[PDB]
Amino acid sequence: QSLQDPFLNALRRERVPVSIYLVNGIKLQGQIESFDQFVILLKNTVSQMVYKHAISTVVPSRPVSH
Amino acid sequence: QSLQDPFLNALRRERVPVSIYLVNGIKLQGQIESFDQFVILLKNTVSQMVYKHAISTVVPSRPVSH
Amino acid sequence: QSLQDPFLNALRRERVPVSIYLVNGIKLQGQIESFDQFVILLKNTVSQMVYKHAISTVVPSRPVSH
Amino acid sequence: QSLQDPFLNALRRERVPVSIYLVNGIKLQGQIESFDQFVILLKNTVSQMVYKHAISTVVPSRPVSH
Amino acid sequence: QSLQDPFLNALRRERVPVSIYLVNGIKLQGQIESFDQFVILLKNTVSQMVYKHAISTVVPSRPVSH
Amino acid sequence: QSLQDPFLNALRRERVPVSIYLVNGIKLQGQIESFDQFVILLKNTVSQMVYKHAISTVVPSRPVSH
């Protein structure tokens, strides 16, 4: 299930800069390189691996249709 | 199960502004655009994807029947 | 399972004011309107939906038998 | 499984005052009245229901064998 | 699975003092008395029961082979 | 699943220094010695065992292909 995948794929495909806010309030920025049901790979200087269980919200930097 | 879906659907359908409070105390605001069992899409300038595991409470801005 | 349901039902039925403390230390107050295994609906001016995964403790404002 | 139950039962049966520390650092005190795999009922003036997912450590006020 | 058990058993058997850091940054110290897949029993003046879901990292006070 | 394993294996095999940020904002550093689906063993002076449920992001100190 089911909503996640089209939303994240749209961001990934359009290479939209996003802000990922973590469960501790820390903000990550970059482009979604790929994802599965457990992690998101977020690209800027290096690819970092973000655990979805530690994500609170994914905020596109501009409107993106899914 | 079972309580969530009528509650969130009522908010979504009536387009009631809500406050979503996260597990770190951060408050999000907007209208519920859609949801499944893992995320809520919360609309204002952009659609942001909120993970339910990081939500503590959903507070309608006015009384809504479910 | 098994302890939750009689405890929360007693509060709900007796309409006992409770304090719900969240995993971030934030205190909610109101009466338990209904619940399932994922959320509690907590009533005051509006019904708010509290996720049990974000609850640390439910504290009745007075002794209640279960 | 398997370690929890003898440990908590020993506390419950011996009516040992405990400190329950939550995942946010908040300390609860009282005696364990009962428990299942999801919650602990902690007694002082009222019985409060503590969610095990929000517990970090259970600390007996004195040595207890299990 | 699979890595945990040899690591924690090595600490337990060698009675190595460890620091257990919790998800809120609080540090516990003592020796691992026993464990299962849900909790660790950590010994100093009393045995305290630590929930693994609230543990971030287990740090031996000296190098231990597993 | 599926993304984690090639990413972490690449770090492990190349012995890339990483920063592991925990869900409370605390940063760990060292090299990934091994991992399974529940923990990562992170090496510096001692091997410490990090629970993946307490990890927010794994950040390689330099670009690594997976």
Image (cartoon, coloured by chain):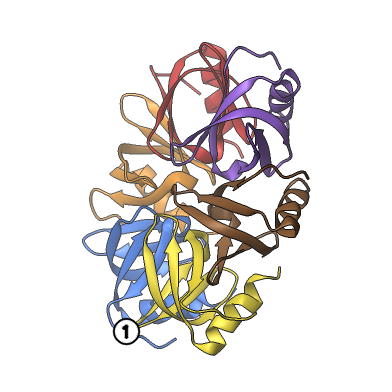
Chain colours: A orange, B blue, C yellow, D brown, E purple, F red
Rendering quarter of residue A54: top left
Badge 1: how crowded within 10 Å, few (<14), some, or many (20+)?
few
Rendering quarter of residue B2: bottom right
**Residue name at image x 27 percent, y 77 percent:** B61
Taking the view exactly as shown, the residue that stands out farthest to the front is D62
Q: In the visual, does C3 lie left or right of A38?
A: right
Q: Disc 1 on helix, strand or loop?
A: loop
**Residue name at image x 35 percent, y 70 percent:** B32
Residue F3 appears in the figure: no
Rendering quarter of residue D43: bottom right
Q: Position of residue C65 (x, y in %)?
A: 62, 81
Q: In the visual, does B20 lie left or right of D6?
A: left
Mark 1 lies on residue: C45
Q: Position of residue B22 (x, y in %)?
A: 37, 58
- How many tags in the picture? 1
Residue B12 appears in the figure: yes
Mark 1 chain: C
Viewport quadrant of the C terminus of chain C? bottom right
Q: Position of residue A34 (x, y in %)?
A: 45, 38
